[PDB]
Image: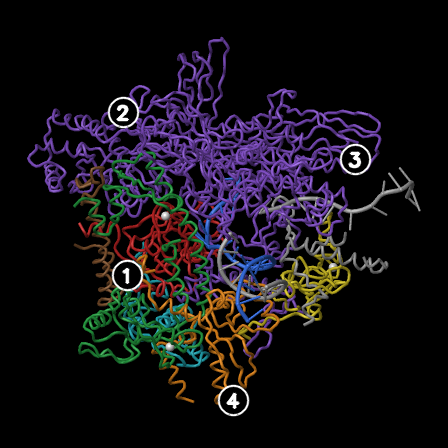
Chain colours: A green, C orange, D red, E brown, F cyan, H purple, I yellow, J blue
Amino acid sequence: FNPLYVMAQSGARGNPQQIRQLCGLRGLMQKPSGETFEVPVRSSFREGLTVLEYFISSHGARKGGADTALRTADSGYLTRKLVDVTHEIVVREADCGTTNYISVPLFQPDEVTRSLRLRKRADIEAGLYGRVLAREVEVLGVRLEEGRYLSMDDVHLLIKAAEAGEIQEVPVRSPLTCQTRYGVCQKCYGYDLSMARPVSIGEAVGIVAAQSIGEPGTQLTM
Amino acid sequence: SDPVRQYL
Amino acid sequence: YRAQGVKLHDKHIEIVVRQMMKYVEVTDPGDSRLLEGQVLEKWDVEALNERLIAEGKTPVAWKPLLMGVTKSALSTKSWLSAASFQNTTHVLTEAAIAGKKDELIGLKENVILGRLIPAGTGSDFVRFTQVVDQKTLKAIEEARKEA
Amino acid sequence: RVDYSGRSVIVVGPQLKLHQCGLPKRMALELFKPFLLKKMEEKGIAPNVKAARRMLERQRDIKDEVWDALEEVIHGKVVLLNRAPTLHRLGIQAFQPVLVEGQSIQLHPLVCEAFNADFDGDQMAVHVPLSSFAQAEARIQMLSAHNLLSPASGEPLAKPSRDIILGLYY
Amino acid sequence: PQEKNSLKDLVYQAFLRLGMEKTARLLDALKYYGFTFSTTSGITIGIDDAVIPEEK
Amino acid sequence: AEPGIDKLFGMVDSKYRLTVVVAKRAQQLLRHGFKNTVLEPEERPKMQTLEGLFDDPNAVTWAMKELLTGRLVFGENLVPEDRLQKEMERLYPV
Amino acid sequence: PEWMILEAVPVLPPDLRPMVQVDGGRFATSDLNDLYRRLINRNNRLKKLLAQGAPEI
Amino acid sequence: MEIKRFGRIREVIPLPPLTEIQVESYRRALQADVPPEKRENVGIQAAFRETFPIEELVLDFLEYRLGEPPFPQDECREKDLTYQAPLYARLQLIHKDTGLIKEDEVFLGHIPLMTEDGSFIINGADRVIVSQIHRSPGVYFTPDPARPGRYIASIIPLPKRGPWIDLEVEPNGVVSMKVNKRKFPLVLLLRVLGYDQETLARELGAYGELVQGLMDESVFAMRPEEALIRLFTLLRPGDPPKRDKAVAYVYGLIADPRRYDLGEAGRYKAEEKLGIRLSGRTLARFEDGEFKDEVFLPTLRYLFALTAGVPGHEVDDIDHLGNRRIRTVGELMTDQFRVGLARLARGVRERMLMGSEDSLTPAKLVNSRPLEAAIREFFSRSQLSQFKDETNPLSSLRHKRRISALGPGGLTRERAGFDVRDVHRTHYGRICPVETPEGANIGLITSLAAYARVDELGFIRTPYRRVVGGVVTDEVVYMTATEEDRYTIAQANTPLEGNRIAAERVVARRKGEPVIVSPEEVEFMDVSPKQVFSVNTNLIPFLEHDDANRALMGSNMQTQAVPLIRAQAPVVMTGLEERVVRDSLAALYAEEDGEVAKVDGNRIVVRYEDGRLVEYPLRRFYRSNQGTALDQRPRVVVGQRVRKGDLLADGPASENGFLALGQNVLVAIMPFDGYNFEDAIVISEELLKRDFYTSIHIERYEIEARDTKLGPERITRDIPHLSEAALRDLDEEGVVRIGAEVKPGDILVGRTSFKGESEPTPEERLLRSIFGEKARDVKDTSLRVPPGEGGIVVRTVRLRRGDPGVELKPGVREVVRVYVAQKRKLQVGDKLANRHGNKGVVAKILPVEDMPHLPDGTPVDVILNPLGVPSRMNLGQILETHLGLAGYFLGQRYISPIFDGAKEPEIKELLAQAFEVYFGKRKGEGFGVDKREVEVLRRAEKLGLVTPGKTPEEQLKELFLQGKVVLYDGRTGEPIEGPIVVGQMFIMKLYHMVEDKMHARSTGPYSLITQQPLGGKAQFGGQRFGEMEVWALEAYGAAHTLQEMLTLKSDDIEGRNAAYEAIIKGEDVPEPSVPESFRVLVKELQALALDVQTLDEKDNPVDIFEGLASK
Amino acid sequence: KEVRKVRIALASPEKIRSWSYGEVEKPETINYRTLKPERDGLFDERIFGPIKDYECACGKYKRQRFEGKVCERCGVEVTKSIVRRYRMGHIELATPAAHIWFVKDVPSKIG
DNA sequence: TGCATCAGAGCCCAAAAT
DNA sequence: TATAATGGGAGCCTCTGATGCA
Ligand SMILES: [Mg+2]
Ligand SMILES: [Zn+2]
Ligand SMILES: [Zn+2]
């Protein structure tokens, strides 16, 4: 029930590396060049640093602050480019009628084992959830029909089916293959992810894509 | 390229 | 994004990549008016080729073209869209020579004009929808019966 | 730049329902001012619109019935709150305003993540949708309580965090 | 114990099964009690709360 | 959350069409002074003043409640626009 | 193609390049007016040098 | 009260004068106190010597003098005048033919004087000139990014004092020189200097393959005249190669000390790098008719030696603080002075042709306007000339010590990458690693370290103690980064007994690299931990326990602290807070020993040893640049014996001479019902009751009455159509009376303006006719209190035309200023912060009965959420709170120095003595442990906080040593289920206050061309709904909301008018029309000769100008 | 009619002259004494329209009963002053001049 | 035909700007 | 409206695309 532990464990605040700097050691710090100092900071913020430890640490802090500062502009420009390219894409009809689709792989070829292994859950969820099935799929004695929006439950079923060797990829409607002019169609798009349900015709889908990709931009590296 | 230089 | 722990649906990235793949380059003109090396939207050459192949003419031979988001954005059919992006003089001189007509298909064009955008409540799909109460509905119906 | 808009410092409002915000009354009187002039005429507070406006001009001439009139004016209406940078569409959300004494806008805890808002001195902008159409769009499409899941991941956006998680965990 | 992940799943599941209006109601409830218990819980941070392991 | 929003989204093929129907109905109510309403005296949305209960002034609140009743019919090409406008003014002048 | 060469040069409406008295009675004006003035001066001088049979230099 | 100070480190020297970087720089520039014959050639003097003699008649410079200021400082601020001195120069005009000499002293205008504290007064406002970091002039060798085995030699002079030269070994093998973007073979330039193949072959032959790339037969064939003409034709194509013209150009490029100036620092660095001695600051000389080389051959020798890998040759680290120097006030100002002087010289030569070549004086020859303009431009419009930050005294002291890499002659913000923003190892002891801006300027704006000083050459030096044998001397040597790199320097905390190093292994730096070392290897030792950080950073107690990212905010936020009427110094100080007040110049001290004769609110009279009676007037309620009140209060009483340096008056934000940026409040660290959420702060109404965090603010309002073509503006009490209610507080003349309370809408100064000629509309004709009242000739232009402002009127200044001592700008009859003051209580939305980077806005003010309270009935002041600590890693605030708890009960304050502070055992010791006062008292008063205290103890032993089996008293003491106490919820009476951390924390009210930021607009002013709303609160502006906001409305599909933003709520003129009219009539808003800025766009494209046509579905023109623009 | 399209095209010297309500023959802006616009200059009311609604410059015709009238004395049309945002003038060049967009935008269109 | 070199194109938002 | 006068002056990033040389 220690406060630090509880905050970290619950996800209320804190993460292990921050707690380590408080109760543990601060650890290795890097020079302005990126090269790491040989001597680490053995102190923790509870014990307190030495002016030399503190000074050795400032380099990385500053580098981080500068990273961050130079990133928000680069991300912003990126976002604006994305907006300009996708703005016209809107959901303009229910079905374009295409027979084309994309097959989302459930297995990534592993180089080190040189055999197929299961893709990570979140990766599969990001490619499957809310998609209309392009072809009929029968796995584990269940009929997932053509034209079915995949619920998150449906996705978990396909993952369990893949673990059982029943299915290695899923045929799915996608904006890549949509034939609607100046936009996509309801089927190729899928769920309006915010409503957990089929997208409404008229949703400005291109803008939402640019905003979705751009918002985390400041969280990447630089 | 320099209008003054040319005129001179 | 995954490395940073950012859950983001492929669907959105696909919308963008699709815009990246929007254009093609003519390899052979066939019986059309097009030129070798001329770049145009994939939609338009597919439409042209079904008009030629249904007309009994040699179709245009074309090649897939991949362009980055900046170039693709600058190449879009809408000149109000392209000129408000970037490279304004270049976009505007080529548009003005060609006598380009902006059809106001996308969002930026209408925003510049202060128009009602073609999305949401502005979509032509829901825009014209009427509401009427049952009293007035039957009242109108009886009026139409007496003619 | 737009009319019928304002800005102030934001402050947390734990007591708010998810569809609410604290809106300072002095801000609300300006943002809705024309509506308030009309309402001040229906009730007898002023002979007409011209007299009503002249009475609101001096702050010492403002009596207590106009505050009650303003409550009537804003009834059922929502305003838009915006925080820069507006990175995605949840940078603007609609709230039904609850008039407050004081000069700070009160923001609901659950929407802080989507706005990336915190209480270290952040400010937000307020907007008044004017028409029935605009007000309908705000209440149906943009209302905070109606947008609970991320358009990007499909995961919950408005969710327990920080102190909320902490109590429940304990 | 309810934490960030279990509580996120709860909101999502409630959205699917009960819809927006009830999930909105559920969130305010979770908000109310979470805040309430957090104040009386006796969560604080003193310097002795950063506990150096003997293993260091 | 707006009362019965999940049911309101049930009624339409596109959430945006609900917004159009709500907005247009509210304009009808305002133009005709609420006297074309499909609500019954006890169903009227109410607002608490210092005096006491009064009618909710808000036409968008009204329009959504009306929609939930089932008494409103919405769609495309239900009736010529002028004919609708004239029939509404005959039934409820301004 | 010859329209890419100008004979008549358009002059923007004045309210879009204003000359305004600010608060203090001082004047504030748009930069285009100075650019137009440079143009007009050189053009008029060109008309005069032409009328007077100036050398080609 | 008692002050207990910790730490064993004895610092042999005090902090330097903190503003000396400003004061000394400018003193050296003006050389005002030096008698002219004794002036060095530097600053203003050096500028004159550079510009003169002006050859063409010859005008020569003798000497300059500075007069006294026409008005004192206080007067300048009052009258919106610049504090400045008259500059004169004795000049002699000579006719070289005749011999005639006329000599005269000409008046050159005024030069601004620096006040005592290192600032300027420019047009009434206090300004600071920020020092600029930049590349030191000199000769550098950097690696060529394209070709790895090659290097670039860069010869850099002072800014604007010459071209940069780049030496490269091209892939073809010939050594190229790049000047003003043109490249040629360097061999040609060597031949002009008079070098021959014999000398060059023997000199550079040692480096095998390179010397042959230098050999070009054709160049050696031609004599120095042909090589010089050849070079001129290469550098200036198309310019006829007259032999005198070529000499002139090349001389100006290389040997001219007027057109080419290496620094004095440039000269030393070159001499030191290349191992030679320079006769001057030029790369070569013109001597005995030819050019004689100085620099080029030594740089070429080093360049080849580097490419070949000869031992002793290095590339240069350009971010090293040996190669980076500071340009202070004197240098910057002198530079602009030199510019104005060059322009004035142009006028002299131009005047030396025209007029009579016979009768001319220096007064007739010199027009000083160019010089006055250059100086006036620098002080008002330069980027390095900034509005002084005087929010609190520490604000301006910090402003004077800031270092910018921006400004004229420096980096842009996008062109500045990581390398410049980095904390270089050489920043140690020189530039603070902490205090820099968060955001885009990070690493570009920095702060001088506390013990740092800028040498005469402009390099930052830091003190170290000499260590001989194992003995630490008291002699301190100030070192540059280059000299610091020679030695092995021990840390300041290395143990000493007497002067001897007491450790077998010491912690030192060699070239910044940390290393463990024997006392025999120790050449120097740090003076103090204080020397690594800025002054603001040095004010944060327990800084060693705070992550640097939060200390950054802590430093910076002390700058934003508002002076409080009750301000107190913190209970945990670092020991710098007295010096800061003294160097700030806010506080008043006694000159010599003496006795106090008189003490007033307005003045203090002191009788010194000399017998002389000195009177000190006190600045009372004066308005700073940021509107905080600067006011001095007498701290002594009549008949008090004072010594030299004893405090007389407290300035703003000081308490008995200690820096007071805030209050010491009782804080509980615990969540509270979500009012604490995400950094919000909960405070007790007791804080307002006792006037903690209350601050005085003064706003200045101004109005002019001027002559018009329509008649005079008049400042008058007679204002058309206003009730006596409206005019009540205006005097006879129309100015609001001192002491009146003014609220928004109220008239401050009454004014009438003559109505612009207009024909009243037929409606007004009929209205005027109906009521039978003549329309007045004048309109009400009166100055009123803006929305949200107001207070008590404390001052009025009225200046008319034609009254003694005052002359206004042309056309202005009279000017009125009204000073309005307000006492501001802390409120919801105001921002608080501590020195550790904890910052939050006040979200809730609870009544005292709801506040968590101690068993003995004491409510806490502030409730801070613990969730703010762990991610931020600033634990110093926790230690401050614990030590603050002990001090609350012991009635004492502490001085805990940075990195040598109070440690945990000592704080526990104090906590034990404190517990005796908090508890032992109760047991004697006849009360035992509370039932609820037992319950809290139960949960606490379940938490492992207390040892099981001990008495209730023993367990409470165990918690108290952990800084936790039992706390009662004032709402219920039941305890908080666990023991909570409570103590005294130092918290400041920052300058960001909701009163200033709250704004709203229905309709208002629109812009001239766009017809869109203006921006900003001061203009009654609208919010900007920008590109990204539009995306948001688009992604929501809110088309009508968006369309409103784009038309009716902005530049749709017809639409916005119709919307307002509809709302006041109760109708719904009409359909929008074309936005006016689209019409502007069409017309702007027509001005560009493009025809933009709006078309219908039939492709027929649609006229959006509605017939108005077509004939 | 409703706007469905926006065309952009090059403008002939003829079209530029058809836009123009007058030629600006003088660099003058406004009179230093009267502050009224200088005739034939950049602000001329005879070219770009009246400064005040339905009022000519010299003030012979001051109200909307004359709309479209051009004062014989002052030369100004009596209309809404809004037209000073709309009406274009022109400068008649003594030598043709190239429009730089079609020169410096690579590859040059003229080139 | 394949490859340097250079000219020209860009580089977050809102607040504020004393 | 007339001694003769005859050639200027300042200067310091990354990607993409066209153009000018092996
Ligand atoms: Mg913040
Ligand atoms: Zn499709
Ligand atoms: Zn006239």
Residues tagged 3 and 4 counted as in contact (Cβ below 8 A): no
Is label 4 in a helix, a strand or a loop?
loop
Which is more foreground, mark 3 or mark 4? 4
Read off the residue under disc 2.
H892
Is label 1 in a helix, a strand or a loop?
loop
Q: Nearer the viewer, residue H1029 or A101?
A: A101
Residue H845 position within the rendered picture, expressed as x and y whole percent measured from the top left: 30, 41
Badge 4 residue CB within 8 Å of ligand 2: no
Which is more foreground, mark 4 or mark 1? 4
Instruction: Confirm whether circles 1 and 2 share one chain.
Output: no
Identity, as a three-letter code, of the amino acid under mark 4: Lys
Read off the residue under disc 1.
D156
Residue C138 position within the rendered picture, expressed as x and y whole percent measured from the top left: 35, 82
Identity, as a three-letter code, of the amino acid under mark 2: Gln
Which is more foreground, mark 4 or mark 2? 4
Which is more foreground, mark 3 or mark 1? 3
Q: Which mark is residue C57?
A: 4
Badge 1 residue CB within 8 Å of ligand 1: no
Is label 3 in a helix, a strand or a loop?
loop
Identity, as a three-letter code, of the amino acid under mark 1: Pro
Q: Chain of mark 4?
A: C
Residue H1024 lies, with reference to residue H192, above or below; the image says below
Mark 3–mark 4 Cα distance, whole angstroms, equals 86 Å
Mark 3–mark 1 Cα distance, whole angstroms, equals 82 Å
Mark 4–mark 2 Cα distance, whole angstroms, equals 99 Å
Q: Which mark is residue H352?
A: 3
Is label 2 in a helix, a strand or a loop?
strand
The image quarter containing residue A219 is bottom left
Residue A169 position within the rendered picture, expressed as x and y whole percent measured from the top left: 27, 74
Q: Is residue H300 visible?
A: yes
The image quarter containing residue H629 is top left
